[PDB]
Length: 189
Length: 193
Ligand SMILES: Nc1ncnc2[nH]cnc12
Image 1 (tube, each protein chain N blue to C red):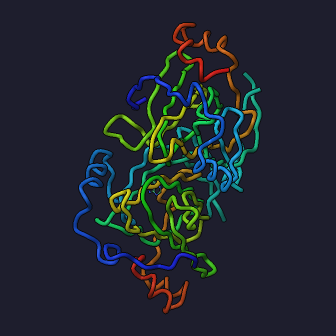
Image 2 (image 1 turned 30 degrees about the vertical axis):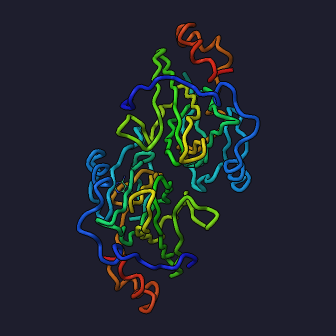
Image 3 (image 1 turned 60 degrees about the horizontal axis):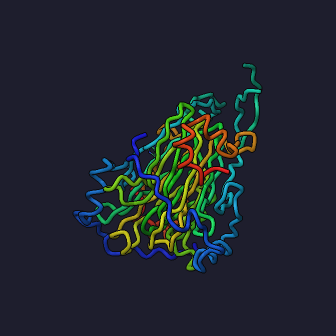
């Protein structure tokens, strides 16, 4: 809790197209649609590898030390559906405004806003622990033509073998009860 | 080195820094509890991974060492402290533009010296995120802008996590000379001593 989930109109019913400025940026930077939704683009992957213990009795797997991506939400596709990661993820706000909703394994729900107006409780830099489900949606905002741009750094570096989607609203019901699950259903597959 | 090469051109602020920072920035400094950094500017370590990693460090001949997997930082340049003075780092550092505008000046051990601008107006060669290879000396300075009241705020991620052994900062222009023509160095002097 803390933020109050109130999806703008384009969040509930996404728009067919994003404003042209966001289109430009999308094409110039060659961002692509992510599995979760929104646009992204891995811009860095450490040349350094590191061995890491991973449960299968565990097993050693090797990953890059770190990975960086640009992640962008837009009226075009404003939601980044509920997904979980093995490693902690660092998020750095760059432009616009958005909101995050985290579902902890014990079933606790947390939601907060991302933006540069810290006085009004807007975070511009946040970390979400591995194992914690997360989703985020675009918040309307001028200043960045209704867009939301952030940078993400994963350590060890991202690897889909470490990524897992919330299995629909079902598993949501299991985690937060039906009444809450229903509320956050728009953020899941 | 894909960043568009930029023209090193300070402003009144840079060469003749202000006495105190402008109210809005000063307020941010107080609220976020940012401290003036050794190399200049203000900062704060926001996140230091609880998870660790063993890394091999030289002392040829080397030896293992434990490091936090990563460190996060808020770095801000203001008209009263507009320069991030030249300094190296064993590891690569990821930089992410957040507010304001600025310019970076790098000096590779080959003597090679690139310089680019940080801003969101990429249609003009400005970059919003950049990685500086360990080993390279980096300096940065403030660029007048209105969006962020002449401030320049970025975030830096270091992995392995920052340790003082990983840090060093060239002194005076002498070392700057034996890295760049004593001439080209003269120009890049305000980012040194
Ligand atoms: N580098 C990356 N590649 C794919 N999905 C990601 N999610 C976060 N970072 C990612």
